[PDB]
Image (tube, rainbow, N blue to C red):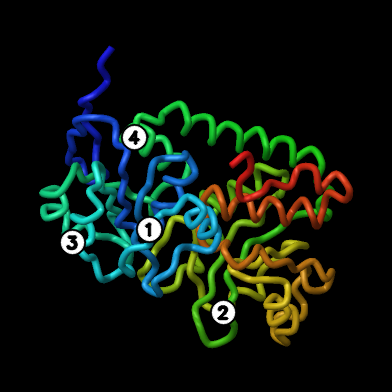
Amino acid sequence: QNVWPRTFQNADGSITTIPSQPKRILSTAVTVTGTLLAIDAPVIASAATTQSTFFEQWRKLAELRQVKKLWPAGSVDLESVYVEQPDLIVVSMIGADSARDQIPLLQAIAPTILVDYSDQTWQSLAQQLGLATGLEEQAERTIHNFEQWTKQVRDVLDLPKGRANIVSYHGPGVVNAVAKAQSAHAQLLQSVGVVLEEPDPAWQAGSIVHRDFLRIHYEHLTQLQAETTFLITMTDQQAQAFLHDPILKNLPSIQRKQVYGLGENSFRIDLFSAREIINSLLRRFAGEQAQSLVMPLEHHH
């Protein structure tokens, strides 16, 4: 019968023994909280962004589930963790929201696990979170339902002819970026039928490398060939700056007026920002097939 206690494999190759199924999960990493919510884990409290907020893709869901907002990233409050009486404490390995250095102190309060969201998809992260929480079946269900959804959406979209690129636009005089072939963004769009133009890895600027984005000198933007451009972290209103950038006036996507914001929450892909992104593709490209496939933040509360 027993699958508790169990031992969780932390992202750094350490381990953490979890004596019983956690029912009071506290997240020290605002980024991880999105995926805890995605699999309906019993999260009772979560740390926040440096700006003391929950990520907007899921904030409303966290508030609805009464997830207590804790400290802003960068100011881990060990005493508030003690107060929450957690039975599982979740820490990220890499990022502003990472409480990795506090693991020894955290482990003194409750079983503390270490996960990495920076180097894998939310889906891969969801599977690991399922093991830590006994929600393996829920993780798979969430992942699979989502996959089936993208298959359904793929069938109803009427995308522009040709290819698209995925750009993070900051304008002239500054490093810009293009989504890489293995990025979560590229995989998501490809899953609903978008055919992508990939960036030249030679364009790499500086020494900071990320899984999702190739960082590049602004001047390389003029070399993009795709007939469509999707803009990271931008609304269509904000996209105007890209459309009206005189240096970019010859881009095929600008010539065709096929430049589209991926939305304010599209920097990082989790279930909820992915949902928003896919919803925007339905509304733009699926016509009156669009609405019935649009997915809410949640339903059947």
The quarter of the rendered structure image containing the N terminus is top left
- 136, above or below 181, in the image: above
> What amino acid is labelled 4 in the image?
Thr
- Residue under circle 2? 170
Q: Measure how far apart labels 4 and 2 are at the Cα level.
A: 40 Å
| Disc nearer the start of the sequence (2/3) | 3
Q: Nearer the viewer, residue 294 or 193?
A: 294
Query: Residue 133 shows which numbered tag?
Result: 4
**Residue identified by numbered label 1:** 68
Q: Is residue 214 left or right of residue 206?
A: right
Q: Which of marks 4 and 2 is in front?
A: 4
The residue beneath circle 3 is: 78
When the figure is inspected, residue 26 is found, relative to residue 255, above or below; the finding is above
Is there CB contact under 8 Å for labels 1 and 2?
no
Residue 109 lies, with reference to residue 171, above or below; the image says: above
Circles 2 and 3, Cβ within 8 Å, touching? The answer is no
Q: Which of marks 4 and 2 is nearer the N terminus?
A: 4
> Label 3 is placed on what type of residue?
Leu
Badge 4 marks a residue whose secondary structure is helix
Q: Residue at x 27, y 20 (%)?
A: 3
Q: Answer with mark 1 or mark 2, whichever residue precedes in sequence.
A: 1
The Cα–Cα distance between marks 3 and 4, rounded to whole angstroms, is: 22 Å
- Say what amino acid the circle numbered 1 marks: Lys
